[PDB]
Amino acid sequence: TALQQAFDTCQNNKAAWLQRKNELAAAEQEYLRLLSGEGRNVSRLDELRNIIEVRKWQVNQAAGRYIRSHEAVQHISIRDRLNDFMQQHGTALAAALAPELMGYSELTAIARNCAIQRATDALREALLSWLAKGEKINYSAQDSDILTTIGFRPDVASVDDSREKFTPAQNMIFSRKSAQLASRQSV
Amino acid sequence: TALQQAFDTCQNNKAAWLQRKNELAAAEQEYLRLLSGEGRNVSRLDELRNIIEVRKWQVNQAAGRYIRSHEAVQHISIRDRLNDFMQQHGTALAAALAPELMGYSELTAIARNCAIQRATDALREALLSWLAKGEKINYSAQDSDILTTIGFRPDVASVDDSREKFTPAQNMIFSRKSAQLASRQSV
């Protein structure tokens, strides 16, 4: 049931990222409205700029968390699907790889690594040959709905908000500022 | 049908390498016979040493040629077996690997390479799990005999005889010496 946990964790990350995005958008629009209002509220403008930047940092963090959760759920789905496929086709698969897979138990570390590398890149070449002809690849029937709901790739609105990286000092400063802002807004 | 050409090239390499080995052994035992005797055949001993050196070089070259041919025939057999198994179960493997394999045709170079790497090392992890659970696998049914006469690995003699390497200058000098020796023996 770990796949369901990954799925709904990704859904929660999507929800949190969207909530952060609309909060930032509302703060941006009210900041522009107040700036265009010819108001003598310099302190108000400064603290709204601070809120804007805190919201941007929170949006970046949420987008990164959602992207990593998407990667994790895709990876676990791949693990399970390939695991059952290989569990069912393993006799033929290892028969096709007998010349460099037998004796794996007693082979040395360097020999084992060389053999698995040769098997791995030969299988890579086979995958490339199969993909060359240009057919259509479909989701597994058991796990089609979850992958369709999650999507093949994360939304482009999640990668453009994570293209810039924050230094650890910036990260901790923004964490303190966000905590202070949350405490102030809670009152 | 190149597998048969690889296999009888392997057999011819047996012929050549065994001929080099037993000719070198005969020359070595004859040299030791003449050295043990009281005969003052210093020129004979010198030319015998030259012959022994060029025969060791020829044995090394033959062992290297065997290693190359054996690796080539194993690679061809692996490619053919992967082609057959992949044409058999590509739909299932694509259903397993769909989360990052569909759309590969229109993806950019870097994305294509990253997806290939992720699929490839996921398959490597699956193969490691199969090896870990400890089930033994025999050779391919279709091509069992061709790859069981040649053996799982090249002979230990072909390995330790080819362990030492020669710089290209040594290779060309030894080629010239071998040509001169062949010309002298022919007449």
Image (cartoon, coloured by chain):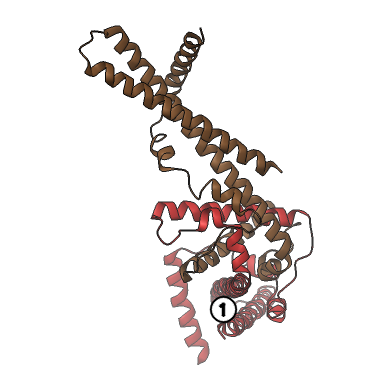
Chain colours: A red, B brown
Q: Is residue B34 above or below residue B89?
A: above
User: Where, by quadrant of the figure, is residue A127 drawn?
Assistant: bottom right
Question: Residue lying farthest bottom?
Answer: A187
B130 up-or-down from A179: above or below: above
Residue most toward the left? B38
Q: Secondary structure at mark 1?
A: helix
Who's the residue at 61% across and 82% down the image? A7
Image location of residue B54, percent across then percent down: 41, 20
Residue B107 visible, this angle: no
What residue is at 25 percent from the left and 17 percent from the top?
Answer: B35
Q: Residue at x 63, y 57 (%)?
A: B116
Please tell me in which quadrant of the rendered image residue B32 appears: top left
Q: Which residue is mark 1?
A: A44
Q: Can residue B187 be seen from the camera position used here?
A: yes
Of residues A56 and B118, the one drawn nearer to the viewer in this rendering: B118
Quarter of the image with the N terminus of chain A is: bottom right
Left or right for A157, reference A184? right
Q: Position of residue B53 (x, y in %)?
A: 37, 21
Q: For residue B97, which quarter of the picture?
A: bottom right
- Counting from the top left corner in percent of width and height, residue B70 is at 54, 42
Query: How far across and how far down the image is residue B103, in percent?
Result: 74, 62
Q: Disc 1: which chain?
A: A
Q: Residue flagged by tag 1: what amino acid is it?
A: Arg
